[PDB]
Length: 475
RNA sequence: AUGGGCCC
RNA sequence: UGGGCCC
Ligand SMILES: [Mn+2]
Image 1: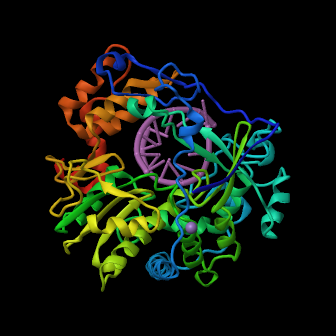
Image 2: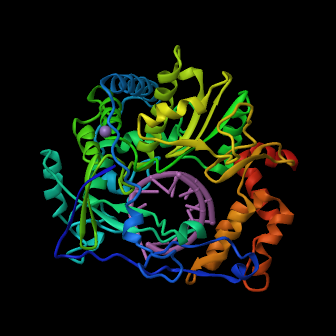
């Protein structure tokens, strides 16, 4: 997005500058090339001369403006995908009830009870529990007063900028490349959920290549599904984006919202409106108030769905801008936000598509960093999706999600105070797919000190998960 | 110390 | 409730 104005204000907002992530016994063994994001301006580890506050916002390189032609083409691609999407999902997208939006419905989890409330509630020193009753699903407004302002299309807000406390590669860490989280007001998240919560639930439950969204999936069981599909195509591309979320141009965002959330698809007219408030935003980082145009904030309720929708529309637009006769069945794809696998029997030229993606502000490069650009021939077994490869399991003959050993070493090397036992249980569910020799090796540093689930136990758990029949078939 | 998968 | 992973 394009930063339009920067200004200071008397009232400073608190920004958390203390990493909870301390190392573990594994850190001494594995010596990962990874470590906590730099949160403090004066961390000893940053490359001098530092300036976090400069790097953090450097992702905003502008707001690409599209020609009339390109906008019309994008509108065709957005409307076409919207057709495919609402065909599969149906058109039951009426406003979710205030109760439902808090409590969730089938395929849509409840709202978090004690997460950040956003602005202006953080200036008042107040938590979500004070503004909303989550056990019940009503009361405490305040909020209602915001509801009405949104209902009357005159609500305004600002995003509260937090620094993401997370493990990152040390090169990123040294360079002060700390990611930021754009916390929206809890009433906005609520209203967006009311406006498009049924739609989001339907997408989650209908995830897969057809709608081109992996949002709602469970890699353990769905890697079989996804893997088999993508193995039928001659060419499979692993497309990376650079700052996908920040570089959505205001024209693309507005048109997507107009075409995908029409009233004629069962949406309340404020569905479109509430999403359109994500385009031009105000952001509060300590004393600074930064106003931005373009880009998606991370804290919206449907951030993943929205990026995923955009991702789908971008690929159709890019292909149609270069080639002719390009339709939805020309290729296949699944996306989770910026993350994407594309495939086609046609020998598509993604290196030539680069400039057409540039017309939307987006910069594509190959995942396989090998000197050359995009090429044909790559199969499903070469690519990554959600930090997981597709490897065929020798025992069951199903695809399983395999994370790279180095990524697992990094995950295991750090933990928040007192979460280490839980962490190892959870992470073993990931590690099991690396095979038993690698599984033991990854957990060796913890033997004697914690409970490490056996390889066999989790293997049998996974067989029943992916295919309950194959589990019984062995017995 | 966001949102939303999923898992415990 | 409270953890972990991915985006
Ligand atoms: Mn624009």
